[PDB]
Image: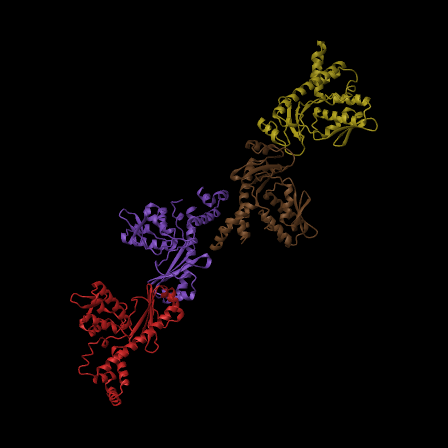
Chain colours: A purple, B red, C brown, D yellow
Amino acid sequence: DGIYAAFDTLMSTAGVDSQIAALAASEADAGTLDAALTQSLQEAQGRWGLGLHHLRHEARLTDDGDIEILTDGRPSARVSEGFGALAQAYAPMQALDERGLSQWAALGEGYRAPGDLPLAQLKVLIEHARDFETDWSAGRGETFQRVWRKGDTLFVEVARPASAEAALSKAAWKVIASIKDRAFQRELMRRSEKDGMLGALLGALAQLPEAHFTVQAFVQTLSGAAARNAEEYRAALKTAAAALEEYQGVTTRQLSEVLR
Amino acid sequence: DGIYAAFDTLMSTAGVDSQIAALAASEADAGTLDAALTQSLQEAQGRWGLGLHHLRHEARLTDDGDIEILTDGRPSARVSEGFGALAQAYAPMQALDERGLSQWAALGEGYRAPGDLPLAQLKVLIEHARDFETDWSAGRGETFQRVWRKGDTLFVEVARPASAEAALSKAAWKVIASIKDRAFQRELMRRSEKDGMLGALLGARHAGAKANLAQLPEAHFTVQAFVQTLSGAAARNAEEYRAALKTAAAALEEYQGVTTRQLSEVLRHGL
Amino acid sequence: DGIYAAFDTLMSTAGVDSQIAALAASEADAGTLDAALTQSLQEAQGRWGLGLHHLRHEARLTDDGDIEILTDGRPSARVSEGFGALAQAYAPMQALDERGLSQWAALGEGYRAPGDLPLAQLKVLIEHARDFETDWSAGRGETFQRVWRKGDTLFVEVARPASAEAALSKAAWKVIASIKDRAFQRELMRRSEKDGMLGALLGALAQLPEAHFTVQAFVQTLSGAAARNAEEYRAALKTAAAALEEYQGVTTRQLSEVLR
Amino acid sequence: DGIYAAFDTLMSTAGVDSQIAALAASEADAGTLDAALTQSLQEAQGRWGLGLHHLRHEARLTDDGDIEILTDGRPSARVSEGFGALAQAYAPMQALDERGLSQWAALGEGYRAPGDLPLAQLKVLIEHARDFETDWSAGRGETFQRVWRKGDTLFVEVARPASAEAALSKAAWKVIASIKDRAFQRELMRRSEKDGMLGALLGARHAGAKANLAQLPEAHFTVQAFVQTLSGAAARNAEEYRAALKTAAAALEEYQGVTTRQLSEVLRHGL
């Protein structure tokens, strides 16, 4: 179950407990496995902060027993090629500004409401518009928020962009601070002075998916009448911010564990 | 030659100067004539007030020298069948409330906002929503309004519902008030108290006038609405929206007055 | 009990639980308090790694209710003048090399055995010499060791020199890594990038005794026949190394607590 | 003049050429004479083998023209009191074992290493210890050794214990073996079998010879030891230590042989 386990780690870098290997162990058929893979990939895309909401992300089993990742049904990458390869495949499809926020609109071509829109106007849009989308707006705790509705589903995205290097540095900091051996810790803190906690931990990388994917956002979804309710929108925004916090903490602790 | 003038008179009831007869006489190719017929009939559909904005309306020439009208690619009627036949074709696809307003949405399936939305909320929708539609207003008399945007075009519809019979009755009231023979007009009013003003007028017309009046398109079609369209940046302008609402209201009033005058001059010249 | 509490913190920087304020609260007389102060000062001198074993360190109550610190009976400093003042008073009496080890001999003038002495020769000196002293020798875990006998007491000193700046940096590292608030921690780690964890913690010093005194050594003492036994010497060396480790850990955790 | 020569003869029993009489005749000031007396007597104390290294030995002139000997600043005897009186003064401060070796330590209170310490351990002590002392060796016959360092000076003491009576007995054996009168020597041996060889010799001496022999310092003092001293770097040299041990042993042998010859030439010249 090598490819299944690799997909499991790829999902775990986004805080997704896909359990794909366990599902394959239960003699699940190709369709059920593909549906689970696609659901996990969509969940992880909602958290990676790549800004590809305009594309349909799917994952399927191939004839040779591999897992293929596709965008809009177009073959994008395969797991056997490595996680860095899949990041390289995703890169040209992205468009990021200096803040790490996606410049693409989730609804594609069409009007986009300004990010500095007053809350009363946003309430009007929520209650009475058909489809709408807002640009990135500043939020609490150095985060950014936006919202868009497609059909009968309202998506609220809260993002704090973060490079993989920063998360690796934070995890290495925590790991170095948590070392029980005094002399070993003093040596690592000494090497850190010269090569960062990066070369401190490594001296004591691309294969690990955490070097390419880290949690940067979270998308919460409302459906039905809840999609047209301001109370539900605010509740979803709060839950999305809390989920971003929780999943970033989970991923940083997981990275610390894997570096230990 | 006759069918083209018949189409022209059908369009004239909706205020459309199609000039199809002139285009036919100019020996224009088929595609141009079908395009002109389709554009004229689509223009007239927004004025007849049938509430069929969700259907695609087309008109094309057929092999046997007639004009065929189609909705959603499905044939509906031929012009030679008569105007009442066209009305009977359009009727089962209508859904009107007690006020004479269409209950169908212009955008089809989807959310429609309530009517009488405050200027602030409607302004937010106009400036920042992608596509939207509102229900009919409460009314300012027998005049109602609604607005919907599709893609890059905003449509403001102002409708004063009126059947062809209602317009003919208004014209009949006008001509009876215009009659200088006081005894004759008093007699006509005495018969009207029993048989309706329209029926009283028709009873004093020529022999077989009812059969000679069903041949006119105005007995089945009349102006019930006016749609004013904005495009581009003006489609997202609340000021342009309210100005277009006023423009459509004034245009509807002018058109209905013109139909009233024409129907009065027809009923008086009858007998 | 301000001066008593200040002396208590001064002893706590060496890991000494002097409890001087509690003793003064029990209406202890001047002699008992002075004896306790002198014992605590000697214990702290054994751990500060200042290399002043050749001097007699005493502490006494003054007529005005202060505490006076003396070397060889000569007034050296007073607690009311501050801990930095006492460090300044101790500084000219010191002699330290590039490794942070004291160059002074604990027995004063006289012969000093080389630090690279073979262990059999050291055993002979332990069993049959009257008084002896060895220079600093390298030991396990980046530590250094030396031994000397005066009269009927054998002292084994194990030292890992460490500046107060390094201990402060290590404590700030631990405190930053232990912060429960994610955004606050990210801000501190960001400021650290520019001003060290020093300005990171301070921006969110000389008055605190930890800025001037930190644990650098430990001295274990044997008496009687145990002073002339090689087994006892090796056991004392092991206990001294373990005590150095334990007290350095205790002081670093205490400094982390006081910076939190 | 007599007391100075008496001190000289007292020193001669320990191999010290004090020349106090010449210094007195040279009219040297008091301080010089006291210093010379003290140095000579301290030199003789290390050869008499009384084991009083822990005491400070001094000699000084007094008001009445005599010489007073002091230990630790306490007066002990005057030279005019006789040499036996000086021996009786020194005796209660001694502590000798059955071998004639002093049980007192040279460094006083403190640790003393066992004797017969292997060359390696003793070498470590010599090179790296500050101050140390060892007990007496097992002996190589009646000759014993020990070593102690104080400050910058190392002392190696080699002792062959012998009372003045023992040295006189050895000299008596020598002179009796030297006697050419075979009948006389056989008679002396016959009396010696009963009264000791020394007593047999003294019985054949002059009248009142025992009273005429107590006036000689050699009846109470004799060479029992030799101390060789190293200073400075040589005080921390094991090779210098062993060389000094050999030097002290040879010097002790030479000194005791000289005393034996002198005592024999005195006993023979007696009668």
Report the residue that reaches farthest toward the bottom.
Answer: B183
Above/below status of B12 relative to A122: below
**Residue B202 location, x and y as percent?**
22, 83
Q: Is residue A29 visible?
A: no
**Residue C249 location, x and y as percent?**
53, 46
**Residue C72 location, x and y as percent?**
67, 42
> Which quarter of the rendered picture does the N terminus of chain C lie within?
bottom right
Q: Is residue D208 visible?
A: yes
Q: Is residue A110 left or right of residue C194?
A: left
Residue B13, picture quadrant: bottom left
Above/below status of D120 relative to C29: above
Above/below status of D135 relative to D204: below
* Between D106 and C94, the one nearer to me in the picture: C94
**Residue D69 location, x and y as percent?**
77, 28
Q: Is residue C30 left or right of residue B15?
A: right
Q: How many marks?
A: 0
Residue B63, picture quadrant: bottom left
Report the residue that reaches farthest toward the right.
Answer: D64
Above/below status of B153 relative to A84: below
* Between D12 and B69, the one nearer to me in the picture: B69
Report the residue that reaches farthest toward the left.
Answer: B64
Q: Is residue D186 left or right of residue B184?
A: right
